[PDB]
Image 1 (tube, rainbow, N blue to C red):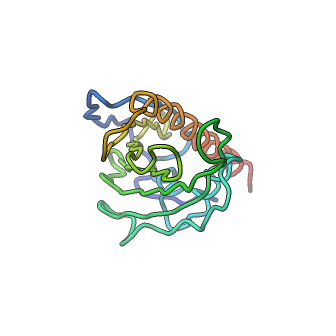
Image 2: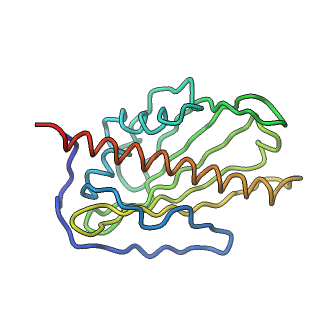
Image 3: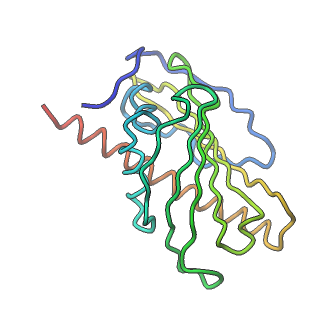
Length: 197
């Protein structure tokens, strides 16, 4: 029942990931049992309801807008922005923050791999206008016509801050949490899809 992209089938592929020294591997070679064209469509294609489901799977995300399609479209250099509110129960700072997300397609080749960069800004938190989280999501062909996912994350600073090492550590942990919700939702969508007909 899911969106398709050709080729529907391919041998396992391998992107080369220029992991920098301030980069952290968030998750590596996480299998998603569906073809690469289908997982790219689920996350990034014209029917944005599946990405919205990824966001609402985490019950701390509230006030979630409709996700726009990519501008100008799902092509290299396309991008999109969307926003939601993240509930926090932090000792410090507010009880919720706007989450400002930006995705840009860096590389797209269903015969090889797809790289999307997603940038998250959380301005309402302490030191929050000074940094952004940048995750590179690589999608590539796995074994038996499935998709493997690898995520690399860094924190980009635009001014100096008091909590750099701490916020980098917390942001890395928060992105592993966010990638786990995206993996669970994707595997749930595919598994419910295979249950139909």
